[PDB]
Image: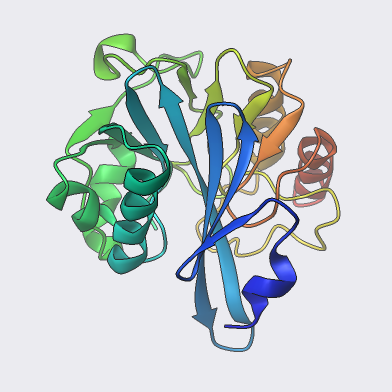
Length: 236
């Protein structure tokens, strides 16, 4: 996979076939790659957050092996216990690795409901959401700076998003595409009626976030939210 070298920027750390980019004093992006027919290596991004004496993870890598490597990198570079992980959609591949490491995992109740038919291991805990989209705090105990928001159905019915309190960063998962994207990608499980409003709701939930991190593109400005919503407008 020679795609990794083209993708790396100054300051990125390669660890096996994983790449880590520091985004803030206590936040890193993790990136893994999967060879997909007719496209070669495709990037998937998540977050690693150092919160005092512990680490919080958002999303697995594509695979269990890659996810184990993320945990290896955390041990080496941060050396704090990983307390919990939040997974933002059912599509994840590395749940077993998190569980093997004794990390408590959380996902939208709907993600957990969809997991078996997707061939995914469910998270151990289900998040539920108020009618305003905000996670019910009893379902997300001790989440530290992670602010979890369900913006409505978009790329998938279960997609959730995560703001990192006290930073410029919000994570849009698969809902948000970068501001240069040519399409919204795979819409097979999308709600094409509500997608545009859901993308805008994510923006309104984290209005101060200037760095938008996403599942399949490098971090971008809020132009990513605007562009995603406008592409989504066209599907209605």
